[PDB]
Image 1: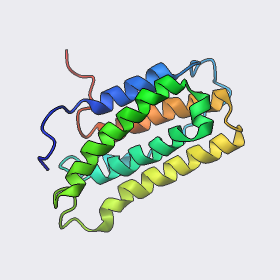
Image 2 (image 1 turned 60 degrees about the horizontal axis):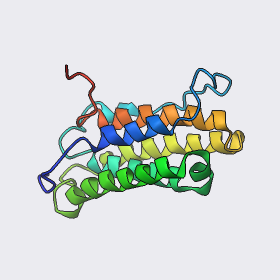
Image 3 (image 1 turned 135 degrees about the horizontal axis):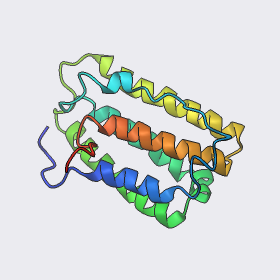
Length: 165
């Protein structure tokens, strides 16, 4: 697609927000260390040409609610989350722009849903981990790094690359 022609580094800012949002370190919370298992299998091939945009949209939508919940809103700074909501809606607006026009969704069969279906099962496990630790600060830290890696893995198909020096 070619609707939004301004910037393309909103994903790096979304993760930068997740970085300032961590109150504790993953090393401090190695008791709740649990890799949920981000489904990058549907984010490594056939998802770098306006084909996984609908997946990044539903992914940022799941992170938008996972973080908008009063449990995550109280788990993180409401101001750091405030900017995180504007960044989630910023990437959601760009991701939606492609979906608005015929672009984004093409002859590609429903197989594209497997990328969103994978991210939905990934976040489903993240929600269970939250209900298990009862929204523990350590569980939220593990979920913080898990959201950062899952989001960087989904945005790795666009510009989420630190290789630039």
